[PDB]
Amino acid sequence: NVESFASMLRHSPLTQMGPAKDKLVIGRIFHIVENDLYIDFGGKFHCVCRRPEVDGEKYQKGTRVRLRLLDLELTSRFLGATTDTTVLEANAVLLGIQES
Amino acid sequence: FRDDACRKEIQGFLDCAARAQEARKMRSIQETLGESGSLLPNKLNKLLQRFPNKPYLS
């Protein structure tokens, strides 16, 4: 009675979430380079959001934030290409700190 | 062509030349070093060579 892979994919949060467009998710900051913040949110790629001016100090490694996802992977195909160009990152908007 | 009756006019042409000369020096150096608006080809071609267009299969 071992769970199959088709049951995991049906009941997984991502699958049920549906289109990421304008979805509120919770991220975790795992790497900071100057103001830019590298954030994981349970997806394949991270998002690189910039430190808010109002309360920059609170954004350290581990801080959990709120995001409004737009894309899970920024891709586009341009004139002459045979495959899509991916920047290996997601697009999202930072909406502050998850105030648990 | 007497420079004793047209003194005021000459200063306008003189002071202007001084200000114009400084702008030329400021503009040439600042534009390349300063980053405003669009990027320069030399820095923009380093970005297009990291994501080259592939009109072939591999």
Image (cartoon, coloured by chain):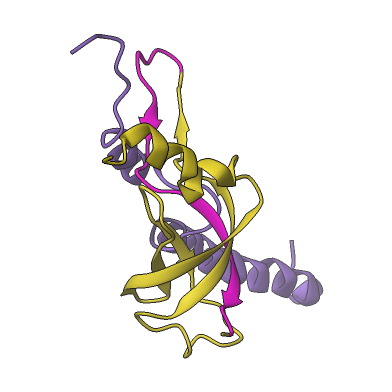
Chain colours: A yellow, B purple
Residue at horizontal 35%, vertical 19%? Answer: A83
On screen, residue A33 above or below B27 = below
Residue A16 belongs to the span the image colors magenta:
no
Residue B31: give x, y in percent of width and height: 46, 57
Residue A36: give x, y in percent of width and height: 41, 69
Image quadrant holding the N terminus of chain B, namely: bottom right
Residue at horizontal 37%, vertical 35%? Answer: A86
Residue A26: give x, y in percent of width and height: 52, 66
Direction left: furthest residue: B58
Image quadrant holding the C terminus of chain B, namely: top left
Residue at horizontal 45%, vertical 83%? Answer: A59
From the viewer's perspective, tell me whether residue B53 is left or right of residue A14.
left
Residue A87 belongs to the span the image colors magenta:
yes
From the viewer's perspective, tell me whether residue A67 is left or right of residue B25.
right
Q: Nearer the viewer, residue B24 or A41?
A: A41
Q: Nearer the viewer, residue B40 or B52?
A: B52
From the viewer's perspective, tell me whether residue A16 is left or right of residue A64.
right
Q: Nearer the viewer, residue B45 or B32?
A: B45
On screen, residue B57 above or below A98 = above
Q: Which residues are magenta?
A: A79-99
Q: Total label count?
A: 0
Direction front: furthest residue: A1
